[PDB]
Image (spheres, rainbow, N blue to C red):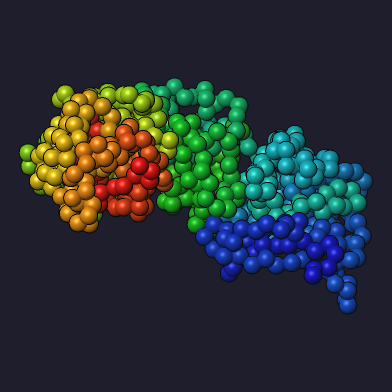
Amino acid sequence: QHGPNVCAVQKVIGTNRKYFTNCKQWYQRKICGKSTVISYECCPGYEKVPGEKGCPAALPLSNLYETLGVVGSTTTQLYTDRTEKLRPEMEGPGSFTIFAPSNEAWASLPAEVLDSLVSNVNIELLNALRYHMVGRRVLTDELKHGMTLTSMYQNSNIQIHHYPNGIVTVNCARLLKADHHATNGVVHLIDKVISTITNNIQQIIEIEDTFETLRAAVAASGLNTMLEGNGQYTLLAPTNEAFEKIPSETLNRILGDPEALRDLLNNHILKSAMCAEAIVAGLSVETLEGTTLEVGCSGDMLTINGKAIISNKDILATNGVIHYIDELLIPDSAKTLFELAAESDVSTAIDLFRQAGLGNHLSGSERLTLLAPLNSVFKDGTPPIDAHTRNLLRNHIIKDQLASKYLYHGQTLETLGGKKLRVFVYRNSLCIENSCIAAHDKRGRYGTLFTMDRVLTPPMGTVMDVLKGDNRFSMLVAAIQSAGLTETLNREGVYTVFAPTNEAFRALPPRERSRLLGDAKELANILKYHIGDEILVSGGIGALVRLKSLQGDKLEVSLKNNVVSVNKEPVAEPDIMATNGVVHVITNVLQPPAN
């Protein structure tokens, strides 16, 4: 095993990026989009001994200036000597903390930024290096609290943030090496050369030319004081180009409507300030609007929902962090029934409504609920726009904007016309007739989109009307009349009739065929076993439902790979909707376990 005082260091394959850790047992296989190698080195304040395993020897404590060379901040050390006032301070008495930028941090600085500092060593460079310093010992235990720090330059604040993944940021500069104790302080190696923060989010929006449209939108919504006031927010600030990409018609409606404008702007604000360096993998974040965004990273680029649309990273504000976004994050709450679904996973259903001349129910201000089946439903093809399909699509539009998680047991939904669909709420399922909710509700500005798992088939007549209208149930209808159950299945109720076809009675042995016809009292009990006490649709089974029958004994109703099975027997045609129940076409007659 590894020797004493050995700390594990996670290095990304083919890059300089290292994640210095206190030899943790848990690891993440991939950082952003690339594989990592778990390397090993000495912990802070220890060195290797030749012939001995690990780092047993403890490094002697040297002054804050000398500890710069130890941690590897040679450039920060060199520029300190150039100021000819900071080196005696760092070598002399006291208690200090220096957030020393790495050699790469100085090399990454733009030509104009570096030139201003190196030319005026006594003015610009001295003040810059003093901002990276604190006049007291500040350790990781304090940095993990995420509280602000007072710098050694005009008592200006230093933003310190801690993240659940363990990453600590100093003005959004990732803390590389930490707690490197000195004779007169502590040295911390940081990812970037940090600068003073003077303006808040609102002031930055007011200064930058790229946010002319955003500035106008904030002013129209009255979110000025919110972006001015003290906080810790993250603004995914959209550029003038992001608004330009969106069609005029959509933008002029959202900018005009105060409800949609407030929702649009709240969808670009996050509750807590998050630096780019903090994001190592996918992370679900809730906006002030309420929509869940996935914040990830593709190497060096920040990404929102797998789309690399973050053009500028970490624009530090007094009340937060600003990330320039190339696209507008329009929430569903601002979009019309069309806009939010036209490009979604129900795009095929939307095209069918459009083709049936029902398009204006998706583009308008009408308060409706759209029952749209998934594209996977039409994998075989789409039905032709005819009388049947038109009427069917008409029954997929519900009066009033509804929410599926607020649908109750005996609820009846009115369609655009007069058809009243029944709501069947189950333990883990929610169905409107045969069709069940397959995805989270898409709540629009005026209408909600209900993503369905199948095309809704509204009921046509009673169980008896269904059975008498099909030649396959001639022997079944004849058996039902002999048993005296014609009235029971023709009247209002909640039944699950597992209807055995003509072949089901023909498949019975010559003994059972003549035997079942002979007895009337036993024939009645066999048929009663095929009828259920409550309505159970295919999408409401889930795993296994022990459905009580009119005979008394339970039915083993199960769903496996979209196939309904009653008493381990398959269903040929499931969910045949009736005004008093559901008909499941079976090819075998069911026998009760007892009597």
Outermost bottom residue: 51
Q: Percent position (x, y) of residue 60?
A: 92, 60
Answer above or below: position of 424 versus 310.
above
- Quarter of the image that includes the C terminus: top left
The answer to which quarter of the image holds residue 51 is bottom right
Outermost left residue: 387
Tell me: 73 left or right of 53.
left
- Quarter of the image that includes the N terminus: bottom right
Mark yes or no: residue 406 visible.
Answer: yes
Q: Percent position (x, y) of residue 238?
A: 42, 40
Observer-nearest of 281 and 212: 281
**Residue visible at 50% across and 36% down in the picture:** 286
Tell me: 428 left or right of 46.
left
Tell me: 227 left or right of 126.
left
Q: Percent position (x, y) of residue 146?
A: 70, 38
**Residue visible at 58% across and 36% down in the picture:** 272
Mark yes or no: residue 360 visible.
Answer: no
Observer-nearest of 370 and 6: 370
The answer to which quarter of the image holds residue 497 is top left
**Residue visible at 18% across and 45% down in the picture:** 517
Q: Percent position (x, y) of residue 247?
A: 26, 39
**Residue visible at 45% across and 47% down in the picture:** 304
Number of numbered discs on residues: 0
Observer-nearest of 149 and 394: 394
